[PDB]
Image (cartoon, coloured by chain):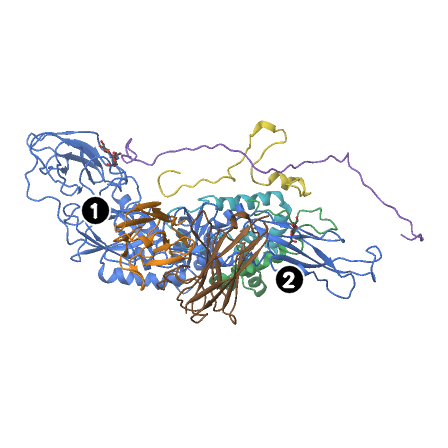
Chain colours: A brown, B blue, C purple, D yellow, E orange, F cyan, G green
Amino acid sequence: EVQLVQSGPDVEKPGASVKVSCKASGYTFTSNYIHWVRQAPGQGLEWMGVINPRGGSTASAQKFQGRITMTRDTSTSTVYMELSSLRSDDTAVYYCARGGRALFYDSYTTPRDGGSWWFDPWGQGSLVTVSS
Amino acid sequence: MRCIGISNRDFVEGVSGGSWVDIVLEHGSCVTTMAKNKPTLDFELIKTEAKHPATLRKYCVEAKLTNTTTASRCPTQGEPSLNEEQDKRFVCKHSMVDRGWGNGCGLFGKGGIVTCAMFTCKKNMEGKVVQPENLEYTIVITPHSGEENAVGNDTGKHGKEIKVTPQSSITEAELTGYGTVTMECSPRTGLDFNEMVLLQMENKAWLVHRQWFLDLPLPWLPGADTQGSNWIQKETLVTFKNPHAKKQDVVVLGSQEGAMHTALTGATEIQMSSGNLLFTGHLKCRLRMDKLQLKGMSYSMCTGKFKVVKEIAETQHGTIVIRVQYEGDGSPCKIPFEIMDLEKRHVLGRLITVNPIVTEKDSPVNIEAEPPFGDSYIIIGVEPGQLKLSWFKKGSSIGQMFETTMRGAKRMAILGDTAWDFGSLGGVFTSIGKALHQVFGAIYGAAFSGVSWTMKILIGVVITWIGMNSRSTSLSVSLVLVGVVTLYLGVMVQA
Amino acid sequence: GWGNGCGLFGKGGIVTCAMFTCKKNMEGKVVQPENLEYTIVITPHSGEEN
Amino acid sequence: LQMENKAWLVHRQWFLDLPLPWLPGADTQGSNWIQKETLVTFKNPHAKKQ
Amino acid sequence: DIQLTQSPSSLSASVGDRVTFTCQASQDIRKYLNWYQQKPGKAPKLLIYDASNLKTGVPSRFSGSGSGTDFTFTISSLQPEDVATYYCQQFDDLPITFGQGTRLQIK
Amino acid sequence: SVALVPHVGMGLETRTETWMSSEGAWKHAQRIETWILRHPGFTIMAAILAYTIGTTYFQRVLIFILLTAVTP
Amino acid sequence: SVALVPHVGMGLETRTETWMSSEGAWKHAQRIETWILRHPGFTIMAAILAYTIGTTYFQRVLIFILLTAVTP
Ligand SMILES: *[C@@H]1O[C@H](CO)[C@@H](O[C@@H]2O[C@H](CO)[C@@H](O)[C@H](O)[C@H]2NC(C)=O)[C@H](O)[C@H]1NC(C)=O
Ligand SMILES: *[C@@H]1O[C@H](CO)[C@@H](O)[C@H](O)[C@H]1NC(C)=O
């Protein structure tokens, strides 16, 4: 089925870098866009960035400019988010999910739209805490 | 009304065609039009708003360095290497110095050496582009005829805002009473975007055509960005010292921001704060007036006894607005406004209120008109003749036609052959004009484009000279055309 | 004009002024052909090691 | 000529004629700068303001 | 840039009631807007797309409305299992952004 | 650098003034003439060249104003 | 501004390299040639002028490389 399994929660020291994984199933792993959305406990949802499984194109939000890399393994049908220079503010839960995708490379607006952003089957979330 | 005082304005007489008219209007300009009927309207052009941009380019005007390891092999053998040369976020260079027993190592020769540096930029340029889509013009089309305050104060509601976008057309507009009006834009005939770039600096922005904005030096970086820090270039930035022999050094280049200003001169700027402010440019609309009442019909002519407030107010060539305040009963009755010669009615003015009208009574209604080149005898009064005001217009016939020709010259310049369209319905020879100058000046004005004041005027005088000494009557095709296009276009441009 | 509100309709004179205060400078100085000196090492050949 | 921490040796005249805001060696408080015409430029869009 | 405002911040209501939310956009977003429900400790969930549209599998009491800058989400009859925090989502331009959220409290 | 490309002839202009607005031209002139005042000899030699080559009087004039233009 | 009069010929030049050393020249060239590529027509007309005026061949060459030197 449409499904997402993220890796389990982790904790890191400030200034560090963390790598969270997003595995998917139930469709063609190259047929949907991936986005990462974060939620701080005392806050709502925040859109971190985007990766396209097909071909590897990527994009990110201004706030995380410089701080976040996205990669994939097609063979495993899995996406990797990574954040650098971890700081206490970064402590939150992270989420990943999809889009119904025209084709090559990632980001569209005009072609209708995805009609979500980590709400349908983005996964189960995972907790990460930046602490000393 | 909302035109007056802006100078530089566009009187368009008559329509014919059964309907329409061709108006070319921009920003600092505005347009006043007339027909043998229908109320005089004014087209004033305000902010142009392009909504959705998309970001192509990152230029940085300033950076800094740190870390910055370096190496040399010392030998002959080898060209030195360093691991951080791998990440292109560094900058790298090879140079050659020398080494030996002083350096301590091998062989006594002129050595290879390298260096790298981490590279990070604080300041940018946001330059984006907009497709010839959702971008829109906003127009105020204002009626004349009284209703106090200001021939001025473009603020305040009369001519609406009449929005338009290429996405739509036909520009259906309404005003009180007569105010049914149909306009048609041709924005795709506008600035020719996709040739265009909107460039936001720290605040101020500039509209410059694409290629130049591609070829411009200084550190490159593509719209995708996204942590990339991937900057190409940097060789024109961050120069490296190599004093006489030993070692070498790397130097932050220093902000060019001003110099960049010096570059962006010769370009109209643009303010951009929220989403767009865009000014300048120009557009072409065609106007179908069918659909217009005279704003009042079958009345009585005033009664009598007007009492004026203030005086004459010429402004550029003509219009002579006057303000008057009617006193009496008769309710919104026509105002018998006339402009006459000395005595012995020859009467000739030309009146632009056309069909002035009293409102609710008390309210300072106003008028504008065009007396002849000479003495003028203006009369609003009827039953006890009520009033007469002496006027004199200086200037003005030959000089008029002359200055007019100057205007039409400027408009042949600046705006091009859209200028030829700026009249209306000349049948054949207007069209054939627009085409002849179309491809003609298309070849000639450009191709010998990209040139400035100096070289323009100078090339002008030289080619007109070689024309003066040419044979076979072709001198004219040299010569008159030459000197004209060259000189006249020489001083008028680059403003 | 009447839009501006005031007098009879012409092209007006206008002025402006601004405070002016500077960021980074250049200190440029000069030195007289005095107060200036050269330092030389005049080294012998012939061994030691060094 | 000392900039923020690099300097340059250049011959006098050119360093006199160089544009950009002038100011004499005395200054301290003077803030007296004589130029500025080549520095801050003034907009005058189509008609009103500046 | 595009600032999505969500109102009100919270509501308490009795079962069966009709409830509405409003989201206001700093720019015209046309028909791109979204409505989330999220229960605590759960991933967010879908409700409304294109501001007008239910998803299949979503109960019918849900609806959405509004066009240029302004929008309203509506539940016809409050139901207890609907206790959650709700959101609206601007997709336009892609500096992807969310509404701050609205919490419910059952009466 | 950006010191020279200063987006001038180009096109697109408009009805409204742009930037340095009736300056940068007279700037251009004033500065090159200044530099002429500073280095008169080069003017001399150049002019001599004008009297040497071609010289077809109008020619002289031309190549002379050239050798004025030649200073960066 | 300082954009031009870049303290070059001047004098005083030392044994040691100065600043942009071995760049700003090939900068200057690359710059202007680029601008030539962008505006070929002006090259054309100018060359024509060279074939018009003077034109004892060497002359043509000279006044042409003015075209090169016309203006960035
Ligand atoms: C330009 O238009 C505005 C809007 O009508 C004028 O302001 C009005 O002035 C009258 C004069 O008594 C007031 O009664 C209105 O209340 C004003 N409108 C407002 C405040 O919105 C303005 O006077 C006009 N310009 C000039 C020069 O008169
Ligand atoms: C640069 O040097 C700083 C110390 O000032 C160090 O913390 C940093 O890791 C270095 N970065 C690189 C890329 O060498």
Q: Where is residue B424? Give x, y as percent.
A: 23, 56
Count the marks: how many? 2
**Residue type at tag 1:** Leu
Residue displayed at 13% across by 40% down: B347
Q: Looking at this view, name the residue that lies furthest to the top.
A: D29
- Residue nearest the viewer, comparing B49 with E98: E98
- Which residue is labeled 1 in the image? B41
Q: Position of residue B226 (x, y in %)?
A: 51, 57
Identify whether D3 is placed above or below B86.
Answer: above
Question: What is the quadrant of residue D1 in the picture?
Answer: top right
Of marks 2 and 1, which one's residue comes earlier in the chain? Answer: 1
Residue at 66% from the left image edge and 40% from the top image edge: D2
Residue at numbered disc 2: B86
Q: Is residue B451 visible?
A: yes
Residue B472, above or below D23? below
Q: Which one is nearer the viewer's eye here, B87 or B414? A: B87
Between B53 and B1, the one nearer to me in the picture = B53
* Residue B388 screen position, x and y as percent: 14, 31
Name the subunit of mark 2: B
**Numbered circle sitting on residue A115:** none
Asked if residue C1 lies left or right of residue A93, the reply is: left
> Numbered disc 1: what chain?
B
The residue tagged with tag 1: helix, strand or loop? Answer: strand
